[PDB]
Amino acid sequence: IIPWEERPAGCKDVLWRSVANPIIPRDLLPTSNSIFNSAVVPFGDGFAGVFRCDDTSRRMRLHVGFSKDAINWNIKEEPLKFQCDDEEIGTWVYGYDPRVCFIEDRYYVTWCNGYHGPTIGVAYTFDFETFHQLENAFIPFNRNGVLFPRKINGRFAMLSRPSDNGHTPFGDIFYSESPDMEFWGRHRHVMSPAAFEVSAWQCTKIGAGPIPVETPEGWLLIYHGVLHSCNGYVYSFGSALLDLDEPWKVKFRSGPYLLAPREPYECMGDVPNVCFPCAALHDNETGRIAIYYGCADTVTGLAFGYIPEIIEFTKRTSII
Amino acid sequence: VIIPWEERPAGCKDVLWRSVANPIIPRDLLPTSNSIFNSAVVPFGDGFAGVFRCDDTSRRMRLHVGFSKDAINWNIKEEPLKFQCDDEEIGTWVYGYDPRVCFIEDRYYVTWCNGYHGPTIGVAYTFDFETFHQLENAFIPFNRNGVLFPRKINGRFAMLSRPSDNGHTPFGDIFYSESPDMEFWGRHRHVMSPAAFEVSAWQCTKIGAGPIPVETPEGWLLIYHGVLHSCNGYVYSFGSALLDLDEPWKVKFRSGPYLLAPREPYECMGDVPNVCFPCAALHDNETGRIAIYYGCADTVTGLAFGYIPEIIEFTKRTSII
Amino acid sequence: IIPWEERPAGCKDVLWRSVANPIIPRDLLPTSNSIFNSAVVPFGDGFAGVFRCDDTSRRMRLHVGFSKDAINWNIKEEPLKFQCDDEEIGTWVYGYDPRVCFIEDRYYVTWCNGYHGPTIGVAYTFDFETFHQLENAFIPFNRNGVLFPRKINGRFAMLSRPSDNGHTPFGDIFYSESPDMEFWGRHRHVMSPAAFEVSAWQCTKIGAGPIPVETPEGWLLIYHGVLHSCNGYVYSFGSALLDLDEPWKVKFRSGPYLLAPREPYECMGDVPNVCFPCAALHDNETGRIAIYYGCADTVTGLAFGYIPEIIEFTKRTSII
Amino acid sequence: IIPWEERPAGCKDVLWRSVANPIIPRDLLPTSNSIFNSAVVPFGDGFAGVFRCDDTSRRMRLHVGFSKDAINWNIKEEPLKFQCDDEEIGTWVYGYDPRVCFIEDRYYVTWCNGYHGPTIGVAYTFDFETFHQLENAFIPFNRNGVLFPRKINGRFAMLSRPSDNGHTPFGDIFYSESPDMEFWGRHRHVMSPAAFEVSAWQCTKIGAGPIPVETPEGWLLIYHGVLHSCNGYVYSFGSALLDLDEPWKVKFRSGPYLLAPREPYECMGDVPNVCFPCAALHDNETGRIAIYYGCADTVTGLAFGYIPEIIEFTKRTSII
Amino acid sequence: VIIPWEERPAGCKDVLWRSVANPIIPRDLLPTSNSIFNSAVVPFGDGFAGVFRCDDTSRRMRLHVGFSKDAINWNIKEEPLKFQCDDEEIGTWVYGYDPRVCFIEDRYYVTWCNGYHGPTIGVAYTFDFETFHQLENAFIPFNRNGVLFPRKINGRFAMLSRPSDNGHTPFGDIFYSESPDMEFWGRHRHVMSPAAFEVSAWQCTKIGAGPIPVETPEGWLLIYHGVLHSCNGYVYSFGSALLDLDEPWKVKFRSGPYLLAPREPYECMGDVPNVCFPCAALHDNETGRIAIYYGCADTVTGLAFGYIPEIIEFTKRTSII
Amino acid sequence: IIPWEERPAGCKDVLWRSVANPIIPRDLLPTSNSIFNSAVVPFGDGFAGVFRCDDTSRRMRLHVGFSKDAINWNIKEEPLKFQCDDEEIGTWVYGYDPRVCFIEDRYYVTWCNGYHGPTIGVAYTFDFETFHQLENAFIPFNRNGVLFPRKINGRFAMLSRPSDNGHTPFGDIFYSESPDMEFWGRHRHVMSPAAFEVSAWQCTKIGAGPIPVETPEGWLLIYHGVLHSCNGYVYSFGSALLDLDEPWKVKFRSGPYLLAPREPYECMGDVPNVCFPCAALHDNETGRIAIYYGCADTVTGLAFGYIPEIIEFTKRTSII
Ligand SMILES: CC(=O)N[C@@H]1[C@@H](O)[C@H](O)[C@@H](CO)O[C@@H]1O
Ligand SMILES: CC(=O)N[C@@H]1[C@@H](O)[C@H](O)[C@@H](CO)O[C@@H]1O
Ligand SMILES: CC(=O)N[C@@H]1[C@@H](O)[C@H](O)[C@@H](CO)O[C@@H]1O
Ligand SMILES: CC(=O)N[C@@H]1[C@@H](O)[C@H](O)[C@@H](CO)O[C@@H]1O
Ligand SMILES: CC(=O)N[C@@H]1[C@@H](O)[C@H](O)[C@@H](CO)O[C@@H]1O
Ligand SMILES: CC(=O)N[C@@H]1[C@@H](O)[C@H](O)[C@@H](CO)O[C@@H]1O
Ligand SMILES: [K+]
Ligand SMILES: [K+]
Ligand SMILES: [K+]
Ligand SMILES: [K+]
Ligand SMILES: [K+]
Ligand SMILES: [K+]
């Protein structure tokens, strides 16, 4: 049973913000400075997740949380530690940008893990108590690693986003596969930022957000895009539809955003003008989807909509 | 013509004061608008018309016509304005922003930052704010902040402009040019450069012309923006200068202080924080009233009021020339 | 008798903001745009200060102010002018970043003085009416000059911060001495920005804030640190303890910040996301300290704490 | 009778260097540092030109020169000074990049003229003794202004190259017309730099060189292209064919260059790795063309070819 | 195999010495070649073969096969090498540079910097140097300086690489990766970073693998390039390291001094001034002789010679680990 | 007796290169990569110097050398190590840019000393065998520190050049005084780069070269200037005359350079297009001066001229 608020009266938008935003405040932990990625999944008869909680030292750590209702979170004060046989991959430097999904028999966590710069860390859990760390999937510099929630033609699949070691001024989404969660390959380009004249909210760089959502015609991808203004980056998010069998083949890609920084909690904070989607919960029998997104790199917010309406919007407004 | 007006508050000593109704145009007036923050406004018939920059939810820059009975409450067309053009190449639409409008002699002219292998100044005319006829782009890229004078200067059309680059330009002088025919342009003259940081830092990075010049007996009143580069971005403020009536590239007085700078929440939070960008004015020489339209945070449109003679006085008193 | 508010009920922070913030508004003077450094000291029956008041031409000027309570200030409308026999040094270009302290027999004012670029200007006063300018202490480019409030083994001492001629993307704190307030030397490195992975609020650049506060466990240094986000700089502030006798030797340095931009008056304004500490009043008998800080380069705020608590926080959280 | 050297036996190149290169040395004048644009034309008995000669102050000045054979030049020691009735336009700041051609009844000179940054200066001369300055054709920033040698459908026509106020990192060629040599307009884009993967010698920026040469198949445009290596720009040059009646319409554009820096005089100098074409003399009866080019921004060189061979090369290798 | 060789010049105390015949390959060997400066060379039958980076007079980067009896005088094919691939997406040619070639078990493999939405490491194999069969690109962009080990390491193929950007990259660490199958890659391990400027400035900006690692009893001998960033550009020098045999990401010794730096006119002047870029080596374990191929000023190819044990001695003696 | 070559026949230049250049080659020492500052003085029976010799690790080290004739040098293989009781200042990181002169009773050496970035190191020797390190004169970032060869009104005096921590894109010359060779002050701006349109060889940055040369008319300062081309920096050098009593007051300053990179040893090497003057020897009786200068940051060269001729050239071509 997923978090839900009905479409506000008179609202014509395909996605609408929770009137209770933010749902997770910056100061939930005794030394939290900000809490703004919430990689959430159903777990048991409630919910679990891995949260980016930056502390008052501005260190980036991951913490486990649990919730009965997916809105009020009980986040562990101790940062998440990963078990690793290999001491060098198991060395912690930093971590941010978590994503979590269930694949076949267990939950997988990806995050941007420091190993001589940003790359994609990978781990699994059965219980959100012990996490077994796997090889980093890629060589740096890479982030916005997002696994598909089932195998594709008998291989694990992940979207990713080649980066640099700074505030990267570019970014294409890529797709890769693995037979074993250890060795990765068959890299395919998915998409590039759009031209400024076509769709400027996604003209500087783009990156995958929540775990891809399967629909009968393809994968619904919710992804961030950046616009470079004279005064900074503005992060908005939107939707695309990927081919089911070869998800690097993009079928439709929204011209308009789904959501952009509007509210004071999106516009003011540690990084102004940021809506960064990180997770979603959905129900295919009602079409309902709830999208979790970071707000100003400070707090966490929720937005709601219907999958069929998002799909119709993505096709009708498509730039491809 | 009855222009909008609010009297200055009790105890306010400022030369310009904001409308208590700001923002006068909201970001979501149209079903697909993301922001509406340039308002090129003129008297038209028994009321007012304008060309508005309305950026949509794809963050595309388009121009839309609007009409108003009082110049405060606007009815803006949902569909973007399309230009008619004799020439297919010039007529091709890439993007448009930064509109300005004025009447010269027998018709309304519209200039805008028109994409043609980069930003340049598009030119068109209209008799009715329904059909627009596009003329040659006035200049080669890169250029924007094109603003016509509202009459010919010694028998030639005249336009202020602002040589630019293809990004968020880190420099910018105002220039003046003439044309006998609205097709060929020349006699380019430098008007002014940014001020020295230690003299007037609100206008030390770059400058550009705003509203159409307003003719006064003490010269053309130019209201123009200026940029300060802080560690966290650009701050856009605006101020005033007086140009020679006959040779308007000769600046006679230029203000040290700004007239208006970002202060209010609607100016300090939005798509581009800390921007007050003036785009149009309405004025009444009988009363000396002036109403200046300005975009706020690249999100919404606001209005500010003052008196022409008080602005002239301020410009002279505080002149850095 | 220093300004004080009790720590809010339930508040676990070492420093807490005044509920009266901002204490100095942007428009206090007829031509002020912003008022955000407040170099304050006790004087006579109350308080005096040197204030950075940027005007509506965005020029950077210094003005003298007086207060009876150190909260409600009466600032002179006319900028401060300095007396100097040397016309070359005496030439005013611009001035910002003032700091003020009494040393032995008079008050000294330092500021970021334009002399072919930013350097540290120096002047004294006996009465806060007439100010007499001394030689600039250093060659450009330097700022964040902050004198010790007594001589150190017989010499005047000053912290500074080598810079460039723009929005400096680096910054270490240095220490220098002078026998005579004219010739300076014995330059020693104090500290550098921390590593991003250890303490990111202070990983781009740092600079000294208020006059050092003598304690039995060392000089308490309150200093700003910068984090470079994709959208610009975020200024926070924290604490270090310097050796009493050789103050370039850092004994303890906080990991977490003491204060970071949170309130709308800190997050929105001429320069968003800035808390810049400029002065402090303290009472060794009660342990109370009141720290003045510029907010968003627009207004002035106050924050309160106890010196023993700040000492304890600095030591327990030390990254060295 | 234009200069000529026959193609060496076995030489397969479309263009070949004079064996006498450099034809103008850097120290020809008592104060010359370098001499490296040579805007040459037939005049009377022999030849005349306008030369960029940078002095030992590294100032950029134009000088008039005369030659019997177009190879050995007698350049005037004193810079060229223009007569102008408008004192504002007639103010000399700097000048470089000259081009000279006869149109109708007199010689026109264009150059990169300082007027609050680079723009295209214009003047005329009947005798190469007195030069009369006209209005600058465009607003800054622009350079590489090159006139057509006759009117095009009753209007003067000029190629130009919108620029910035530095070492410009971009550059498209544009075309403009004027009824009167005063007011300019009908601006049209001619061509942009090529894609890196298609033709990298011309992928950063391009600019017109010699006066266009009229042929039955279009205007022969010889133009420079830049490649941005890790160690700077490399200037090469190539060929295109423009429509006769509407010269902004490009018919053919070479993939390969015609000439690139190879010789020590091209690869070592004030600006290493530069071949910058500035003029040509040609003879339609024989098809001979002689192209003048600056070498390393230090000296002037000559290269030879046949117009029909250049045309066949431009077509065969066309990237349009 | 008879590897090229010249004895050390009389009086010469350097560990490596340039051929007196340099450049051994000129820039205009082919009718349309602009420059020829990577030479990925191996023994083949009775002579030598290689894959050469020949940039053309359009300044396109292509790979060409060549053959030589002596490894000094090369017969390079006029037409660029084409790869067979049955996946059209991966088999699309955009550009290629930076080849390296070695024999592993049953065939020759060739890696190169292959354009696939930016630089990455392309991989192919050949049995005969006539037909080349392309495999998956080994990594996601941006990467280059991919260099295979000449045997499997504990049953897996192994490759050095170099994470990059899509420009003239201002950074660069060498990495190591493994693959069981020449298709999927993983077990990524950091090998080394640029040195500190105050320790060894020829290798302080970025580093990258050069020739195929050469196996010694004392480790893998890695010859690699290093960049120094002067006010006027990058200077590429090359030096030596020894890697653990079994875990080649563990560096045992790393030279402080360079082995070779741009000195000669053919190294200092050309398309990219001040570049010595090593691309291949031939060696003879019986004699200890090694011949190192290197690109000179991105224009021509040179040769340098030395003795493996003397290089090992120098690497240990001068080690900055 | 200082080295001398008479001006080549007909040569009209104020300064002329030695026909023996380069006088010091790059490979004098077993591990030298380049040898290109040579801070030279008369000593005992001949000459002594401190030389910048970068090694084959590209480390910057200073070495002592001696010569009978000041042309052919015997440079010590071992780098120079300074004696210093203070362990903090005595720590060696790197050193370059040496300058040497005799002041009153001993030889002083300054150099660009690494101390948390570049600053001016200072030391003395009586014998060119043992060198005794003093305090760094300034806080970083600074270089091109050049002492005057006597006291000025009872104080030691030094030119310097505020910098940054990279390849500095700016640079003015400053003057400072010290009563004791420990504490420094009375900082005065000497000169800034010229405007591009006035004198482009010196329009990016400038810095002092050889020790100032006393004349009856003022101090002859030989200094470098930088021009920023598209392909890098070009270092040339020229002359100014400073007031004898107040040497920050410039009396005349040359518009043209004295010398600029022309020869292959100046235009090809580790840093192309560099002539960097570092020391001079002179004879007041004859007016002869021999100027040592770094060539392409690879080798050392010599140029000769006459002090009165240099002075008249500086006056006649003065840009102030
Ligand atoms: C603590 C901090 O500033 N972290 C940021 C991270 O939030 C961001 O996503 C990345 C890219 O812009 O840069 C930094 O790693
Ligand atoms: C869509 C968008 O971000 N447009 C901006 C425009 O508003 C701005 O005026 C111009 C110059 O700074 O840059 C961009 O074109
Ligand atoms: C008027 C203005 O913008 N002044 C700022 C000043 O506040 C700031 O501290 C300094 C460094 O960032 O740069 C500028 O001088
Ligand atoms: C003196 C000097 O360096 N002049 C150059 C000029 O030669 C060049 O064409 C232009 C663009 O790169 O920049 C500068 O004006
Ligand atoms: C054609 C051309 O300039 N190619 C270069 C290539 O040689 C170089 O290795 C790379 C990194 O600097 O940049 C470009 O791809
Ligand atoms: C080894 C090396 O590259 N040193 C240079 C030095 O020669 C130069 O003067 C300084 C300023 O450009 O930068 C670097 O420190
Ligand atoms: K795709
Ligand atoms: K003017
Ligand atoms: K210290
Ligand atoms: K065209
Ligand atoms: K390692
Ligand atoms: K001076």
Image: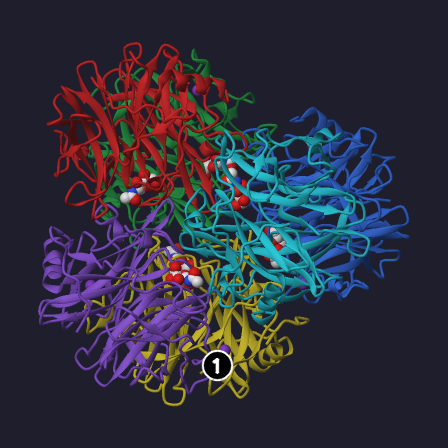
Chain colours: A green, B yellow, C blue, D purple, E red, F cyan
What residue lies at 23% left-to-right and 55% top-to-bottom?
Answer: D259
Mark 1 secondary-structure assignment: strand
Q: For the N terminus of chain C, give its image quadrant.
A: top right
What residue lies at 27% left-to-right and 28% top-to-bottom?
Answer: A176
- Image location (x, y in percent) of residue C55: 66, 64
In the displayed structure, E41 sits above or below F127; it is: above
In the displayed structure, E132 sits above or below D76; it is: above
Quarter-wise, where is residue F320 in the image? bottom right
Q: For the C terminus of chain C, give its image quadrant.
A: top right
Q: Which of these two is toward me, A259 or C49?
A: C49
- Image location (x, y in percent) of residue E29: 18, 40
Q: Amino acid at mark 1?
A: Val
- Image location (x, y in percent) of residue C15: 71, 36
Is residue F155 among what the camera can see?
yes
Residue D141 shown left or right of residue E49 in the figure: right
Is residue E122 among what the camera can see?
no
Residue A237 shown left or right of residue C136 in the figure: left
Label 1 residue near ligand 8, CB within 8 Å: no
Crowding at dot 1, Cα within 10 Å, few <14 / some 14-19 / many 20+, comes out as some
Q: Chain of mark 1?
A: B
The residue tagged 1 is B214
In the displayed structure, D141 sits above or below C200; it is: below
- Image location (x, y in percent) of residue C90: 76, 63
In the displayed structure, C53 sits above or below E212; it is: below
